[PDB]
Image: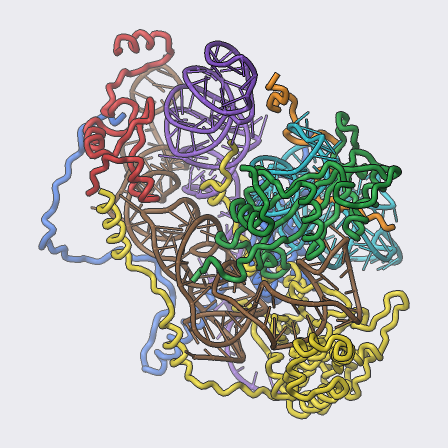
Chain colours: A red, B blue, C yellow, D orange, E green, F purple, G cyan, H brown
RNA sequence: GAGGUAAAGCGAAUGAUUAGAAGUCUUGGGGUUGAAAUGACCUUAACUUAUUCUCAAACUUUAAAUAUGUAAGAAGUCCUUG
RNA sequence: CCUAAGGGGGACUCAUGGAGAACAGAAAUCUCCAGUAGAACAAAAGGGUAAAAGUCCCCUUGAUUUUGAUUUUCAGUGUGAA
RNA sequence: GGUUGCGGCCAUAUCUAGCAGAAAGCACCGUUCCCCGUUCGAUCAACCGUAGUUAAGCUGCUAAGAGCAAUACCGAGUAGUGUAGUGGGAGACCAUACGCGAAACUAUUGUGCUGCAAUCU
């Protein structure tokens, strides 16, 4: 994939850097936080993305939407 | 085609505040203005009568005339190399008392109150305000506060 | 199928009306027109004759406006009338007249304008304004405030208006809203207005219903039946009430069987109290735990 | 007899076709064929 | 509290509106108004088209329809006379989500009034607005408010009340 | 006191805009069901819900820095009364 | 451009959506609910306006008389407008 | 303390869904001779307070509620910016020096207060 982007760099003017992200895929979570929230049941799939548990709002709907949520 | 009408460029200045449209609270119509009062000018868009020109939006002046629903305010405007006194007629919806008076009027009474007491106690007191002076010496004790050593952090990319 | 309307964006940008406008009680357009004083009369307050009609009561207050809130000058209630000899029909047009007269006399006694500005002594139903006495204090000037109540010729608010005007208050008005005004021949019939002043319409109803529908008479005019009050002698009840009000309009508060503290302690018993943050946190924890 | 008329409360002073009155938006009324 | 079988929760007819939407203005509309007067004993009101539509052949402000509102016992009498024509047989999809209901007669002479060939025959829309006591809360000028959720009229309550009062069948 | 520029925002109004997911199609068609039932099924397209990527000189809840108005007393404050 | 589209007062609430009613259907009229203005306010655009400045009804001529003051453009002249 | 009338600030007050409300008040509630207004006493007007009810309105409470408000070893002294250099860089732009300094985000808390008059178990 890097070599794919390195070639793409030739089609652009200016300087571009290829950077390996610290985050899991396109999520805003670092690769260890995402694993922790996955094993804590706080993250569910939504197709090509995910949805994260909120400690806010209606309690009942929150519980139904995230069944595997190990509360602390 | 230049356009320089009366209310040109007042798209945002004469707008009502967000979630503050509609009727005017009546404390505006209950305040009493006397000749010689210091008032602030802020045009209210919902009242198109007695509206100041955009120049006077945000200016402070002296009330010199009081009429049925308005006050006459005096503003000094720079026109070239001198000031000109302008006499603006404003409905009281566009006018508010200037709060700069009250703080100074409080100091006038406060100063007199302190001064007369010093005469009573046979002492003297200095009434002039003082700018914040440099701070004096002090001793910093370190029980529970042993200094933490901080160092600059290494560069790291956070995307 | 359609966009859900009550979104969080709808709530965020909603500008709630004024507190007493959302209550549906204050018309701020009319309030602005009434309260606002000519700025060159710097601190002289305008006085409002606030007239309100409940299902069981008439309230007539004299009010001046201030930034902290309105301040009551004097007040007259319809449930004061039993002290003055009117026990029934406390929401008549004539009860309204009595309340207006009472508030007028009470305010004038509070000011000191009793010898001067006695008012219309011989209530005849003529339209008339409180005329100022030369070389003396001007009559107390009050402006009628009917709130959200609709203006109709024959309405009870103008009964309070007429009572106050006959009591010596200078309340500007035109006679085209009194019961008895002919629009086609623009003059005020004094006899019909006088009839309405002294309960003539109620007496006529008793006369008409008694000899036509006696059962409805027994159900409706019961309190008059147990009082042995006939249709003919009602006029004298209001006539004596007027004289009694003019004799002594001062305010007598009702004796209270409990102290303010006793009332507060009694009422505080039936008031639910808000939960502690800890209590509701415990409730949330219990609900989650019982959800597994 | 008197002939009262229902009073107008709407604000559309213009003279045009009503909002959301398009053709083909209807179901097939002869879908039973 | 909040007892379901309170007295004041008693459903009863608010009003009955009779609508004849004759698509033109003139003799037909005047005769329809005559029919409405005969049926109700009240002068009806003539409603105007809001916009011009060529397919329906109407223009703005042409007095198209006529209608009248009846309240009280007269509404009940007219409603039962109209339910006879429908032989006390309504459908589940004749009741709105707000608990109102309505139907339509095709020939007004079936209501039981003298037939005049000159006047002709018209169909008619009966609409019954249901409501409990305390609806004045939403209509009075001062202190106007809304009606609580329990006190609201809905489809199932209206259907049950209709069946109980009329022993009629609602074809679900 | 005044301001609406920089910045910011778009799971905030207006406008622009990428991608799926779950639903409703009952007011989208196609195919396949039926001897005829619009009553289903597979499908794409529509909408709705919760998300998602990216924007605005003539969009905006928010909102600087700099610049800008006024005041800082004897022509003042207070007390009494013509 | 307007004798109302000016003035005063009063009553009412708009765009739109949903759920319903013979002909009637995506579009006629009627009813209820929701509806912060997503409507309308002669004409550009911007601002403003909800028991109204919007829709409808009642009465009107203040779109009148006298000559001063003030604001904008500004020389602090005129004209216009306020 | 509850309630009414009139208010001040104008969501910490609004909105959704539930539950409770003693006294009083308010309210819904009843009637159409009269004044008055309507297609319609529904709204408005008048009359009774008499026949009834807290069902609703109203008030309070509940919600890991929506919204709103406030606070911050939250983000962040970041973005931006005033001033400076014969600083860097081909440029685009960037760093540094002396100053000022956000917004979103995150988290926590809160959910009307109050004036005058009257009234109340």
* One can see residue B67 in this view: no
- The residue drawn where x is 36% and y is 80% is B119
Dividing the picture into quadrants, the one containing residue C163 is: bottom right
* One can see residue B27 in this view: yes
Q: Is residue F56 left or right of residue C132?
A: left
Spot the residue most to the right: C185
User: Where residue D33 appears, x then y in whole percent?
Assistant: 61, 16
Q: Is residue E166 left or right of residue H41?
A: left
- The answer to which of B127 and E172 lies nearer the viewer is E172
Task: Work out whether E103 lies above or below E137.
Answer: above
User: Where residue F45 appears, x then y in whole percent?
Assistant: 49, 18
- The residue drawn where x is 80% and y is 39% is E63
Number of numbered markers? 0
Task: Work out whether C84 lies above or below E124.
Answer: below
Dividing the picture into quadrants, the one containing residue C100 is: bottom right
- The answer to which of C217 and E58 lies nearer the viewer is C217
- The answer to which of H33 and C47 lies nearer the viewer is H33
User: Where residue A9 appears, x then y in whole percent?
Assistant: 33, 10
Task: Work out whether H59 lies above or below E123.
Answer: below
User: Where residue C236 appears, x then y in whole percent?
Assistant: 74, 89
- The residue drawn where x is 77% and y is 88% is C121
- Name the image quarter holding the C terminus of chain C: top left
Q: Is residue F57 left or right of residue E13?
A: left
């Amino acid at each position: 994939v890097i070599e794919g982007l390195r070639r793409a760099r030739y089609k652009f003017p200016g300087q571009q850097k290829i950077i390996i992200s610290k985050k899991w895929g396109f999520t805003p979570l670092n690769r260890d936080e995402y694993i922790a929230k996955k094993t804590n049941g706080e993250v569910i799939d939504d197709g090509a993305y995910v949805k994260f548990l909120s400690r806010k709002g209606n309690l009942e709907a929150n519980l139904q939407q995230f069944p595997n949520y190990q509360y602390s | 085609g230049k356009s320089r009408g009366y209310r040109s460029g007042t798209r945002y200045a004469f707008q009502r505040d967000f979630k503050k449209h509609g009727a005017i609270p009546l404390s505006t119509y209950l305040k009493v203005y006397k000749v010689g009062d210091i008032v602030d000018i802020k045009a209210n868009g919902s009242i198109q009568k007695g509206m100041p020109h955009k120049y006077y939006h945000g200016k402070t002046g002296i009330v010199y005339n009081v009429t049925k629903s308005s006050v006459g305010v005096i503003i000094n405007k720079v026109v070239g190399n001198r000031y000109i006194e302008k006499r603006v007629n404003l409905r009281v919806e566009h006018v508010k008392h200037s709060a700069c008076r009250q703080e100074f009027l409080n100091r006038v009474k406060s100063n007199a109150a302190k001064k007369r007491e010093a005469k009573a106690n046979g002492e003297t007191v200095y009434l002039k305000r003082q700018a914040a002076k440099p701070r004096g010496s002090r001793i910093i004790s370190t029980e529970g506060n042993i200094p933490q050593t901080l160092a600059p952090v290494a560069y790291e990319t956070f995307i | 199928m359609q966009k859900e309307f009550r979104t969080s964006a709808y709530h965020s940008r909603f500008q709630t009306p004024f507190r007493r406008r959302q209550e549906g009680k204050t018309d701020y357009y009319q309030r602005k027109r009434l309260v606002t004083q000519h700025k060159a009369k710097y601190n002289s307050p305008k006085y409002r004759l606030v007239v309100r009609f409940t299902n069981k009561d008439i309230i007539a207050q004299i009010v001046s406006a201030h930034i902290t809130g309105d301040v009551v000058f004097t007040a007259a209630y319809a449930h004061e009338l039993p002290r003055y000899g009117i026990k029934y029909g406390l929401t008549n047009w004539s009860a309204a007249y009595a309340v207006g007269l009472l508030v007028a006399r009470r305010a004038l006694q509070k000011l000191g304008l009793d010898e001067t500005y006695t008012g219309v002594e011989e209530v005849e139903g003529e339209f008339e304004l409180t005329e100022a006495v030369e070389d003396g204090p001007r009559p107390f000037k009050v402006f009628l405030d009917i709130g959200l109540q609709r203006t109709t010729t024959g309405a009870r608010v103008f009964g309070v208006l007429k009572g106050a005007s006959d009591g010596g208050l200078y309340v500007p008005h035109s006679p085209n809203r009194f019961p008895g005004w002919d629009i086609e021949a623009e003059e005020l019939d004094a006899e019909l207005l006088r009839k309405y002043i002294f309960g003539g319409h109620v007496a006529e109803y008793m006369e008409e219903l008694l000899d036509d529908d006696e059962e409805k008479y027994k159900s409706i005019f019961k309190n008059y039946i147990e009082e042995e009050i006939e249709s003919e002698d009602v006029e004298e009840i209001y006539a004596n009430a007027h004289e009694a009000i003019r004799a002594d309009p001062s305010f007598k508060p009702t004796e209270k069987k409990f102290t303010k503290e006793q009332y507060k302690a009694e009422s505080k018993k039936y008031r639910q109290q808000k939960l502690t943050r800890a209590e509701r946190q415990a409730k949330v924890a219990k609900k989650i735990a019982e959800f597994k | 007899p008197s002939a009262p008329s229902r009073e107008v409360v709407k604000k559309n002073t213009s003279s045009k076709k009503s909002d959301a009155a398009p053709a083909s938006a209807d179901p097939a009324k002869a879908k039973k064929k | 509290s909040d007892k379901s079988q309170n007295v004041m929760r008693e459903l009863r007819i608010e009003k009955l509106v009779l609508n004849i939407c004759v698509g033109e203005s003139g003799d037909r509309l005047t005769r329809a108004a005559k029919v409405l007067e005969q049926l109700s004993g009240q002068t009806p009101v003539q409603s105007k088209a809001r916009y011009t539509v060529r397919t329906f052949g109407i223009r703005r402000n042409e007095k198209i329809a006529v209608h009248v509102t009846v309240r009280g016992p007269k509404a009940e009498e007219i409603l039962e006379r109209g339910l006879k024509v429908k032989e006390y047989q309504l459908r589940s999809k004749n009741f709105s989500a707000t608990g109102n209901f309505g139907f339509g007669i095709d020939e007004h002479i079936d209501l039981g009034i003298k037939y005049d060939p000159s006047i002709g025959i018209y169909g008619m829309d009966f609409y019954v607005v249901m409501g409990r006591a305390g609806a004045r809360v939403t209509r009075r000028k001062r202190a106007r408010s809304t009606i609580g959720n329990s006190h609201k009229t809905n489809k199932e309550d209206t259907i049950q009340w209709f069946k109980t009062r009329y022993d009629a069948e609602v074809l679900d």
